[PDB]
Image (cartoon, rainbow over all chains, first blue to last red; front, side, top):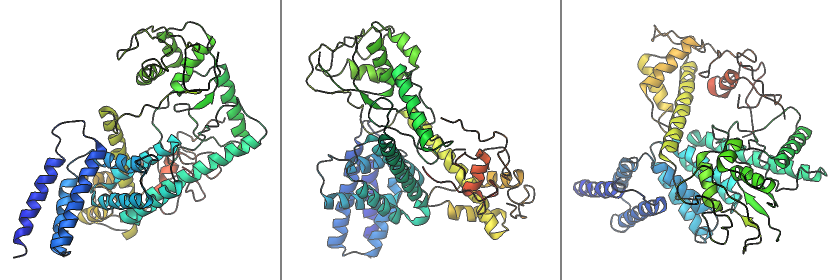
Length: 438
Length: 60
């Protein structure tokens, strides 16, 4: 008799969840979406605890329904990562320590319900890397505690890679800070700009596959040479990843009244140097001489002349949504400004990624996961030194369930590659015969 | 400062063939290992037969 109402409530909850997470309409706020899921979960928990006095069957039913309707959205983990990242960011409504802890506990509980935890882990790593690069950390100890709690909730086997990556990132950040401090004590420098030395290895970091190249002016060239010399004087032979794709610096540059510190991006740095040294530079010539991305050029144009009237000292032709070739602009420092330092506001749009960019990132993550699964598949066969056609598939699926979803194609590819690369002493023709070589 | 030479064919005995199936990870001497060697020493075998000595890499 207790069963009969379970079906009805499960159906109602499933319909409500499907309606809430439906794709009808666009521009859904990830923060509002996660808030709605949290509110629904809280309402269900209150209903279960109040009237159903913590019944096991109802808990199992609601857990099954949540697992069913949670993975209906492929992009859902990314919004979860954004919600758990911006909330931890400073200035998020001034959340108290208890409130932050409760929000993190709820986020960890939801992360337990996600079927595909690999995408969630990748998104969390990317968000953590972005927050670290944002140079706006609220509490590093709080972030470490949240990471440890999430790893404990998700399981040691599943989150060992995430914990190792977080420890490696923390160690790399500490080493970079120590190296910068030593170089400063080194009784030397390369131009007096802000020590934004991102000389860190990209072995286990979420570095972009493409490294933009920025036209280094004579001052930027001297700064790069000095930085390279200091790095050689710190670790000879070793060369960490210090690409200028996201290079940042803080220096005072005058284009030819009041002294101001200019803050520009890596792509905008070439344009500023061209305007600081030369008088008239065409947009096409500047882009050709710097090879800046079209999106980067558009963002720089929007943040330079299309922004606030107080910082609108140049009238680009045309300074609108459209981009016109040969846009002649001049950096007029005589214009009246309010802020002492001219810092370009960061382009922080709504949480999310471009559809082609998101698809490419998902494809890369899936390829990496498939490669890791293929590599780990041979480990199961090597541990038992023997496996069958179904036995190997079952063993692979045992280790490829929490992190991702096992596929027969991946198992077949791993079996073929074991014979091909001679890593394992198996035979592609004889599936029953399986052994280990390496 | 210094270029990275991980040997396109093979840096040393790796037992992984010249392929990505079996560079980013730093070597023991901080001179970088082969792409096949790094992949073999990452998660392929418990005992790394890819850099003579056991190779596990560190740092992000």
